[PDB]
Structure formats: C-alpha cells, structure tokens
Length: 367
Ligand SMILES: [Ca+2]
Ligand SMILES: [Ca+2]
Ligand SMILES: [Ca+2]
Ligand SMILES: [Ca+2]
Ligand SMILES: [Zn+2]
Ligand SMILES: [Zn+2]
Image 1 (cartoon, rainbow, N blue to C red):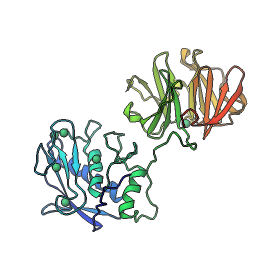
Image 2 (cartoon, rainbow, N blue to C red; image 1 turned 90 degrees about the vertical axis):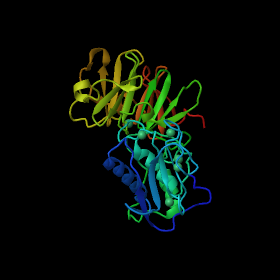
Image 3 (tube, helix red, strand yellow; image 1 turned 60 degrees about the vertical axis):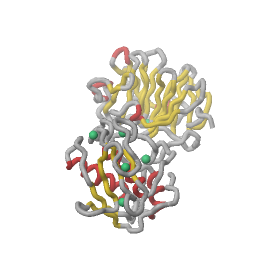
Image 4 (cartoon, helix red, strand yellow; image 1 turned 30 degrees about the horizontal axis):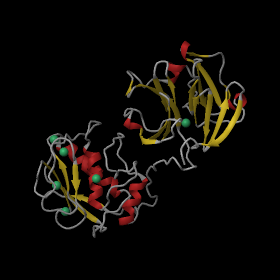
C-alpha cells in the first residue's frame, strides 16, 4: 500500500456523505446500494463510520459528471478515465466524481459501480495507488464478481485510522508471491506448453523452457469460475481444461466456460456420492488414463471410454511410494508426474514407480 503524499486524514471518525445526482444507467436504488456497500468495506476494518445525508454539504460529495465539470479534472468521454476522487480535506476534499459517459452497471458488465466506487472512496480516505496486483487500490479494473479488501488494503487504511473496533479483526486475502518458499498450491494444470499454478483468486503461469512468471486473477481468463479451485487438468485431445470445485466441474475452451457446465462429478465421471470434493487431478500425455486424488485414496478414469476402471478406489501411499498419502496438486510434464503437497514437490516416474527429485513447491520459479 501507499499513503497519499502529505498524509491527508479526516479529523472526525464519524463522516457524512451525499449523492448529489444519479446516473441514468441504473435505478436510484441500485446506485444507493453500490455506494453504501462501498463505504461499508472501509468501515468494517476501521473505526470510521459513514452517514448518508440528503440536503446540505457533506464530507464526501458524490456525483456523476460529464466532460469538463467544474473542478480542473475534465473527463474524457466514453472510455479512458472512469472516475476520480479528492484527498481528505475541506471543500472539494474527499469528493468522488464518476464519469457519466461511463456505462455504470450492477452486473459483471463493465463497469460495475460498486467496484469502481469502492476504489474511489479509497482515495477519498487517504490511500493512493498500491503496487500489489491483488489490492483494491491497485491502478486498474478487475472484477472477480465479489468486491473485497485485500490484506494490503486493510493495512493501508488501518495505518491511517487505526484498526477495527471489532474484537476479532477482519482479514483479507494476501497476494501469493512466487519467490516465497512457503508457497503452496490449490491446483495445477498444463496448457498449450505452459504450466499454470492456482492459488486462491490468482494464478501463476510459466513456460519451463524460459522462466518468466505471469501473475494475475483467474477471472482475467475465466470470469465464470468460482474462486477457490481444488483440482484441474488439461485434455489437449479436445483442447479443453477442466476445473473442479465442491463436487461439480467446469470445462473450458479458449477463454469461455463451455455450454451447460458446470456439471456433477458423479454423473460426469461416475464417482460414489461419498466423495465430497477432489484434491488433485492429472492426465497421461497419451494413454487416455486420468488420475483423480481424494483424501488418501485415488481413482482412475478412462477418457476414451467415458468410464472409470475395474475397482479403482485404491491407495495412494501404496502405488505412489514416497509422495505420502495426500496430494495438493499434480500435473504431468515430459512423462513425469509432478506431485505437490504443502511446500513439498516430488518428481515421480510412472514407469519405475520411483521418485527422482524432491524439491520446494516454488522451485520452478526464478528466485
Ligand atoms: Ca471516460
Ligand atoms: Ca468534501
Ligand atoms: Ca452513462
Ligand atoms: Ca487441491
Ligand atoms: Zn472531477
Ligand atoms: Zn485510483
């Protein structure tokens, strides 16, 4: 996080805010809701409170304006700058302006008022742009269908006003770092020559032949998917990639969730209704066998037969000597299975049912 130069800060802890005019793009109700919830994100992690007023001046004056609109920060029509807010302070201080030749929404369509307002109000309280890609204050517009403060945002805002008067203290997701040797993965899959690691709302993509890591929201590519993947694998045969969460599984082609999916695992792969979820999955280069891992047991399914194999609720620790009895993630590369469990990574050889290397979970990255 980065605190606005000069460290402007509101002196009162009980602030007032007013919505001057309303955008035509939405019903007043929807605008009101967006703003309210935007303020709440901030009041949840600090002692500050925001009260909506109707008449008269307020600390934070909110408005929808078009082009040059009386303040020296002219808007640029459709596109470009969506909004801007001023530092805490008297007058125009703390005010937020949304550019009206923007198409404010309440859905996944660009640009969602709640999301942009949550960000603007940040500047309204004294925060500047963060260099943390996962932070709400980051300079951009991403939409993971659920606006929330990243741990970085909380630290930034608490540094100016103190922490929540909550006895528990809210927390926010932390952005994974590739050079942290404490890194662990929710799931991993290969895709058109690259390896794609998943962790919370993020993903880390790499081509092992030229180590250079790409970090970003899973929603940048597949907005439909629910954040919190548990397993995943590629099936280049159909050029798809399947993700598992809960007990249903989404399939994807290119950058769009295929028709109908999600779908049930039981009806799609044939798995006893006993299995709640899944821990990890991989598919053999060109053998047609796909291995799914649950708990300490594993199962095999034949793609070219839309069906499992004769009695397969077998043991992990037994047929995969060395990796232990629980898989966090796994993917295949050049004939070897790469198993992940916590920060541990075992390079397993299918042929010799042998373990060649035992590395750190993030060993692939350049650190
Ligand atoms: Ca604009
Ligand atoms: Ca003001
Ligand atoms: Ca508009
Ligand atoms: Ca997992
Ligand atoms: Zn303005
Ligand atoms: Zn900003």
